Amino acid sequence: GNYNYLYRLFRKSNLKPFERDISTEIYQAGSTPCNGVEGFNCYFPLQSY
Amino acid sequence: ASVYAWNRKRISNCVADYSVLYNSASFSTFKCYGVSPTKLNDLCFTNVY
Image 1 (cartoon, chains in turn brown, cyan):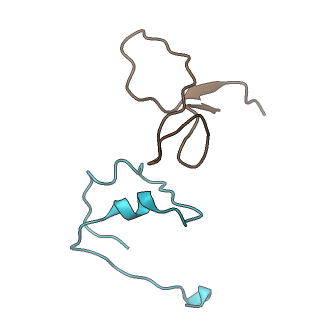
Image 2: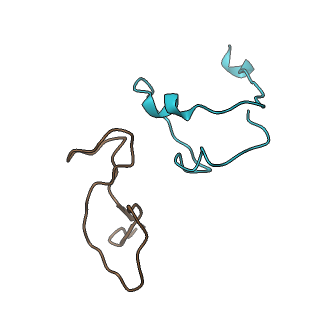
């Protein structure tokens, strides 16, 4: 299998045309405020194929 | 009830209260697969089971 290729799955807002963004900020998906820690409330914006 | 005899309820004519779900600490899993948990409150449905 191959898992070296990833894509962005969460973002606070949609991209404008020809924008580019590489930040790995922890999106506050869950009800509690994320403070630099992962969990069931906080997810990483990137997922692999 | 017994697992081979699992229990069922039809629900209708009611206003969902997802706040309890989002606030729940005790659950081992709360996960929706057909629609995202943020898109719940603004969708309406004709039955729920």
